[PDB]
């Protein structure tokens, strides 16, 4: 029974570090991974002692309900497959509606495509980082409102 | 070629950093190892100001041709971490005053690239994940905190 927690879909480098950063801030995280029985083990240890890894498929809404999407703070589609991330978002919008969704893009080319599934937050690691680099090198100061603006869709 | 930026690479990160720098009004000199044909396609994707020097970033003579002696900073943004680390070393061998920026293609290479001491290190996956965590945790990120994440 998970509540007021974050659900992370995926086991990519972006997903793992986001889970760790969330744990470090005292947040509860529930991970869903389609990895093999053997790999789930290496991942649970890769994460820590309070690792809540639900072996399964996030495209399936029954696993999402199980993971607790009804009581989470947000669901994060962070795998290296943009088709699965786009779908995780669709499934979620189809279950609750008011649930907050975050989606990271693996291939910057797909950005306009995922815009179509309307996630609350979109993160393209390559474009976000390049835009920030451009500003910082240009001596421009980036305040909090500018940063959040590059994330909110 | 003075008071400008030099980007070594033609990866997705490289191209968008060049585009973003141009939009901010900054001049940029791009060096890539792409074949004659691919070079042409690259210049067209970078607009009319496309200053593309087909060559080898590891060769300090192409770096001089690109104007590292008079640049604002040199950016190592290709998808090959060996080449990015070498570009940095090359730069520190010429000016030792030239600002170096390096983007890690493979997160596992982070520790080994810190050994070449670049001025700025951008690990896209780590940077992005950390900012997501912060924002979802309700924190506010000010320019100082952001910069700190980039400074090596």
Image: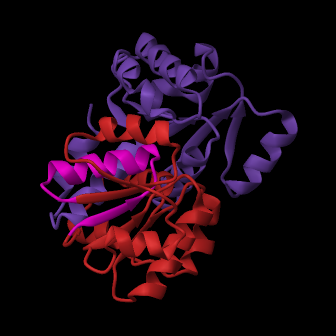
Chain colours: A red, B purple
| Rendered view: B90 above or below A7 | above
| Rendered view: B74 above or below B4 | above
B132 left or right of B10?
A: left
Magenta-highlighted residues:
A5-28
The residue nearer to you, when weighing B75 against B72, is B75
Q: Quadrant of the N terminus of chain A?
A: bottom left
B56 left or right of A123?
A: right
B94 left or right of B130?
A: right
The residue nearer to you, when weighing A150 against A29, is A29
Q: Residue at x 31, y 81 (%)?
A: A70
Q: Residue furthest top?
A: B93
Q: Residue at x 58, y 14 (%)?
A: B60
* One can see residue A45 in this view: yes
Residue A16 lies, in percent from the top left, at 36, 46
Residue A84 lies, in percent from the top left, at 57, 64
The answer to which quarter of the image holds residue A116 is bottom right
Q: Is residue A20 magenta?
A: yes
Q: Residue furthest left?
A: A26
Residue A69 lies, in percent from the top left, at 34, 75
Q: Is residue B81 magenta?
A: no
Q: Quadrant of the C terminus of chain A?
A: bottom left
The answer to which quarter of the image holds residue A73 is bottom left
Give the total number of marks visible in the rendering: 0
| Rendered view: B40 above or below B75 | below
Q: Residue at x 53, y 36 (%)?
A: B77
* One can see residue B3 in this view: no
Residue B133 lies, in percent from the top left, at 25, 57
């Amino acid at each position: 029974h998970r509540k007021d927690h974050f659900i992370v879909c995926g086991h990519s480098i972006l997903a793992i570090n986001t889970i760790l950063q969330l744990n470090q801030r005292g947040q509860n995280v529930t991970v869903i991974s389609n990895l093999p029985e053997d790999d789930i083990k290496q991942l649970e240890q890769r994460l820590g002692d309070n690792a809540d890894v639900i072996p399964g498929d996030s495209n399936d809404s029954s696993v999402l309900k199980k993971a607790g999407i009804d009581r989470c703070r947000a669901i994060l589609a962070l795998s290296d497959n943009d088709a699965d991330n786009a779908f995780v978002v669709l499934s979620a919008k189809d279950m609750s509606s008011d649930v907050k969704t975050v989606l990271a893009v693996s291939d910057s080319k797909n950005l306009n495509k995922i815009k179509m599934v309307h996630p609350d937050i979109i993160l393209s690691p390559q474009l976000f980082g390049s835009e920030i680099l451009a500003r910082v090198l240009n001596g421009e100061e980036i305040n909090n409102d500018m940063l959040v603006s590059m994330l909110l869709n």
